[PDB]
Image: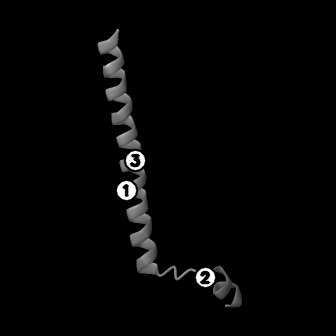
């Protein structure tokens, strides 16, 4: 229990599930946005060529 107080994270079960869900959807959103950025950049490069 002292180690638990040391780590200092509430880590509630409901909080755990919610947090993992939100951060994972953030991860996928980031990846998709980066892919969109790459696609648009390639389109612009094609336009220049």
Residue that badge 3 annotates: 30
Comes first in the chain, label 2 or label 1? 2
**Between marks 3 and 1, how big is the CA–CA gap?**
8 Å
Comes first in the chain, label 3 or label 1? 1
Work out which residue is located at the far front of the displayed protein and give it. Answer: 48
Residue that badge 2 annotates: 8
Which percent across, then down, holds residue 14? 41, 79
Residue that badge 1 annotates: 25
Residue for point 42% across, 57% down: 24
Comes first in the chain, label 3 or label 2? 2
Residue mark closest to the camera, 3 vs 1:
3
Q: Is residue 26 left or right of residue 2?
A: left
Residue for point 36% across, 22% down: 42
Work out which residue is located at the far bottom of the displayed protein and give it. Answer: 1
Asked which secondary structure carries label 1, the reply is helix
**Between marks 3 and 2, how big is the CA–CA gap?**
29 Å
Residue for point 44% across, 65% down: 20
């Amino acid at each position: 229990l002292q180690e638990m107080k040391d780590i200092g994270v509430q880590a509630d079960a409901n909080a755990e599930m919610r947090a993992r869900e939100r951060r994972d959807r953030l991860h996928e959103a980031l990846s998709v946005n980066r892919s969109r950025v790459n696609q648009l950049e390639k389109q612009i490069a094609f336009c220049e060529a």
